[PDB]
Amino acid sequence: DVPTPYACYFQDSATPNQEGILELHDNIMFYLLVILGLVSWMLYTIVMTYSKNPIAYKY
Amino acid sequence: ESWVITEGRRLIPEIFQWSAVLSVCLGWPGAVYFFSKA
Amino acid sequence: IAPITGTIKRRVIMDIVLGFSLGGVMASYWWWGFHMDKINKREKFYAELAERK
Amino acid sequence: NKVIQLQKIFQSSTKPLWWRHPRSALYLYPFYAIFAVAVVTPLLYIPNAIRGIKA
Amino acid sequence: ETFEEFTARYEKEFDEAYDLFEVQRVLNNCFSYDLVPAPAVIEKALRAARRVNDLPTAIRVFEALKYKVENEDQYKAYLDELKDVRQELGVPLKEELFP
Amino acid sequence: ALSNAAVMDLQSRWENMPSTEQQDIVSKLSERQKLPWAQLTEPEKQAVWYISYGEWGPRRPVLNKGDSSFIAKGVAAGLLFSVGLFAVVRMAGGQDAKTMNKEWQLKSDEYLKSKNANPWGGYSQVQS
Amino acid sequence: VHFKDGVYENIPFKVKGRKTPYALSHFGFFAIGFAVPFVACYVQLKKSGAF
Amino acid sequence: WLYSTNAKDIAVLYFMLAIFSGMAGTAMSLIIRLELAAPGSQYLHGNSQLFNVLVVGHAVLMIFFLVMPALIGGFGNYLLPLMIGATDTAFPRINNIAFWVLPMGLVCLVTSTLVESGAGTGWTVYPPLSSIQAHSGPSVDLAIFALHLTSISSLLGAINFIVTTLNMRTNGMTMHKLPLFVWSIFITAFLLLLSLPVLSAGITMLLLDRNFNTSFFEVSGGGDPILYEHLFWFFGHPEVYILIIPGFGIISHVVSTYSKKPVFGEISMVYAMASIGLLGFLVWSHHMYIVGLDADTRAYFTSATMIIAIPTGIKIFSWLATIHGGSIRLATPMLYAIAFLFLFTMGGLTGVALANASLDVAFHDTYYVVGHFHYVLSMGAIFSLFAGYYYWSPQILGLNYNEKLAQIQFWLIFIGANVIFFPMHFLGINGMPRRIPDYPDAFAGWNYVASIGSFIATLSLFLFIYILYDQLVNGLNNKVNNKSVIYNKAPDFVESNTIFNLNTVKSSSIEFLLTSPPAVHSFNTPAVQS
Ligand code: HEA
Ligand code: HEA
Ligand SMILES: CCCCCCCCCCC(=O)OC[C@H](COP(=O)(O)OC[C@H](O)COP(=O)(O)OC[C@@H](COC(=O)CC)OC(=O)CCC)OC(=O)CCCCCCCC
Ligand SMILES: [Cu+2]
């Protein structure tokens, strides 16, 4: 179809072959936001809460 | 009695601040589209 | 006097599972408020093409 | 035969090791003649190769 | 391994300290573990500082004890427990000194 | 004993103290520590903690106190000198495409509306 | 460099004691490396009609 | 000096060229991104040539002349002699040809543009595009030779590292106890050895099909161009797993130094680091899913290149375990190594989305790929190169680098290159193709967003030149005032300040126990370990 200025998603699905991709691009990115949701959280609990820990648990 | 209210107060303004990072680190194209649609 | 142990163990289990609970409130909205919102429009328009008989 | 003989010359020579052979004076000045030409003439044809002037 | 094998091992190593170095390098790894040290072993962490004639490595005990106590309620009961051997040696704390 | 006018305010005085005197005071203090404690006076007691566990040389912070703002004033003045340098290379730029000036963009919409290009979604195609 | 492990003597530069200031010979190594595509955008446009 | 065979002074020549090829490799990317600022050819007048020349001119300076000679040459010829316990490399005379063919690999490439044609073939130099009927002049003739000089330097530059690690260690340095930067390059040296002779046949056959007309690849004769798509990419995926394994060595040293703690699972980190190198061989046609492979061949690769995400998860979750308990000293190598742990892993999630054969068929050659491989090249192999320079600059040069000025160079790289490479995922999910000087008008949205950022990152690089000027001129007047950080490990809580200056460097490697700068003979006695 036609691309849209300042767009961020797929072009409009006009094929079941194309319609399968949109339900697999979202099936993948649902399991990519748990991993990005973990890493973005497990890196803010370390840089903030453990930069003020002067006794390093080195064992 | 210790980790029921001291483990909370360390974490309530943390997730109040952590979401403010991802709305700037990842949500920043939701402002340049908002500002100038022309 | 109290043999207090497990200050890091109580800050890993509390630390991991509140990221999985934070990996859901960004992902279950993305699959419902965006993905099911996008399948709402395509189920609507294709039902407005089968109306023409 | 010359292995002990050269070992007197090579050890405690106080020379660069590529000047430490007795049969090495003639090995360099013809070699520095073919080295002084093979690194300019592939490069001097490069302004000849910019204007389409080929052969 | 356990809480008691933690206590018996580091209350033993404080006796053969003999120096300022082998107090601070042993007071360090008596505080750099997952758990919290008993007041039995920290009594030999003040007697070790008295054997080496150094006071700020006995004021730094109670400041390392303050951050790694995980509860203020579990600190004042822990502070009043040590007040029997903290008034003999005359060790102040960092908040009372106001440096 | 040790006099008051040598350990009075050993916070602002430890640095910019001459180095031969700077380890003379730790020599006098190391002999006052071979005593029963709680007989050292408080300017002599709080100023042996500053020598062993203060903030000077080692245990100096990675950033100074007036230095975290100098970081955030080089970032926010690097984005300004970036965009301000972007305009000079754009004003020294070639002539743009003819298909962008809001009226080519307008008539390329009912061309798509008469063909139903993006039914659900937007085919606006308008960004002058 | 074979010997003299000093402070400036493991680098083939000549930092101190140079006749000319070093910012001439330091920016003049890194801006020259910046200006090599701007002569590939010169002799390939002027050859191919553009300017 | 020019032809001194000391391995220390060769690696300072490696690093002296990887910025000169860097400031040429990013000045080309400046003009590339300046042309994608607006529709219509703005600065290039109407020339769609010299844009497939600048793209190949930029993408090979970044891969083969920046990240290859720095993470393997600029560091591996300085640290693998030093950390293991050698005096220099095992083959020190061929150690000098491995550098001095690299400027000769530059004269074979800058003159490949100045000649009348210009090699407009792209980085993946494809056979019928680069055939003699398509590309006529001597432009692509030199572009397939400068790729050969670097193929032969970094090949004998890895034979130099298998017979250095295997026999030239110290007394107690057993095979299970090495620094992880050595196990990075020694594992890398078993990929540089077993992928570059595959490449050297895949380029010389293209030379034979261009002036000796042998038809390995010519269609008139049955020679496939699709043989090239599995023979070049058999080199290609191990090549991009060579720009990241020394990147996995520097980060494992920095993140466990600026946290006062040994690294989590060191024996677990060396077995999941060759398994990346071994299993990276068996996945080489995931780039070419759409080129017409079989329905079971693509079914194998869509399950096999996801298993590369099995040991990389071990090598990331352990870096989120080696800083959990310990302290954090946020200096400049710790800032890069902690933003490497967020932007490389987001370049990994886009990896497993592209890894499927059922989803690459709507993503190949788009800008969603360029959004993915720049989060793992300019953010996974520059974030570990800036975290390796700043981690060993005053230890090796002897001069400190104005720490208050290296923090603003980090943030202008972080947010001034995330603004470029994050909107690339949006232009590619619509379907903007690659290597194009102009585009449809709907792709002018983010291509002006990604154009404002290339002046931000290349203003930080102009600042990084000034840090290199402040480090060489009055870099001695930095550690005597409060400009820089001197001790990279602050002492413990109960470690007194007057006892710290006796036992200063509590390192786990020899690299800091040496002098600053190290001696010309820093090992004249066989050192002992444990
Ligand atoms: C090592 C790999 C590498 C690196 C770092 C970069 C860095 C950059 N690249 Fe490039 N690029 C490629 C490899 C790389 N690229 C490849 C393989 C292609 C595809 C070509 C093809 O297939 O057609 C490509 C293509 C490519 C395109 C075309 C897309 C397409 O057609 O496929 C564009 C345009 O936006 C682009 C831009 C940039 C930008 C803005 C940077 C910025 O990051 C650069 C500015 C940032 C810096 C300031 C940091 C780097 C500067 C240094 C000097 C390094 C520092 C190190 C030392 C000094 C210690 N690149
Ligand atoms: C330089 C570094 C580098 C690295 C490390 C990678 C790593 C990976 N790459 Fe990429 N890739 C390139 C650079 C790199 N790539 C380049 C230059 C190209 C081609 C561009 C060109 O042709 O011009 C390319 C191309 C490319 C393609 C081809 C697309 C196309 O051209 O059509 C594909 C698709 O399969 C792909 C996939 C992957 C995968 C799956 C990984 C995986 O190794 C990454 C896995 C990492 C993680 C997933 C994150 C960490 C792990 C976790 C936190 C836990 C596990 C994760 C979950 C359970 C989800 N890459
Ligand atoms: C091809 C190669 C090209 C290379 C060109 C790159 C140019 C980059 C130059 C960067 C630079 O040199 O800055 C370092 C310099 C010295 O700093 P220092 O580390 O010794 O510590 C100082 C002290 O700790 C705090 O300094 P103080 O806080 O007292 O000064 C305020 C200062 C802060 O504001 C800014 O940084 C942005 C303006 O403001 C000014 O001075 C305004 C004066 C007009 O700091 C300065 O004074 C910068 C002054 C402005 C220079 C022009 C800026 C252009 C963007
Ligand atoms: Cu790949």
Image (cartoon, helix red, strand yellow):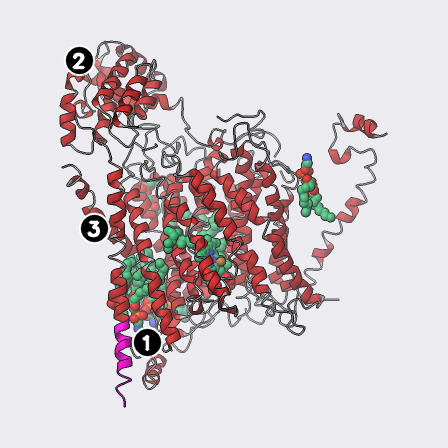
Chain assignment, label 3: B
Q: Look at 41% across and 78% down and name the residue there.
A: F98
Which quarter of the picture shows residue H250? top left
Q: Are marks 2 and 3 on the same chain?
A: no
Residue designated by label 1? F126
Q: Are marks 2 and 1 on the same chain?
A: no
Magenta stretch contains residue H83: no
Which quarter of the picture shows residue G45? bottom right
Q: Amino acid at mark 3?
A: Phe
On screen, residue H389 above or below D2: below
- Where is residue H261 drawn, in percent x and y? 37, 34
Q: What quarter of the picture does the N terminus of chain H occupy?
A: top right
Foreground residue among B10 and H93: B10
On screen, residue H112 above or below H157: below
Foreground residue among H521 and A45: A45
Q: Look at 13% across and 31% down and name the residue there.
A: E73
Residues at marks 2 and 1, CA–CA distance in whole angstroms: 84 Å
Residue designated by label 2? E88
Residue designated by label 3? B16
Chain assignment, label 2: E
Q: Amino acid at mark 2?
A: Glu
Foreground residue among F125 and H222: H222
Q: Nearer the viewer, mark 1 or mark 3?
A: 3
H389 left or right, relative to H228? left
Per the image, label 2 sits on a secondary structure element best described as loop
Magenta stretch contains residue C42: yes
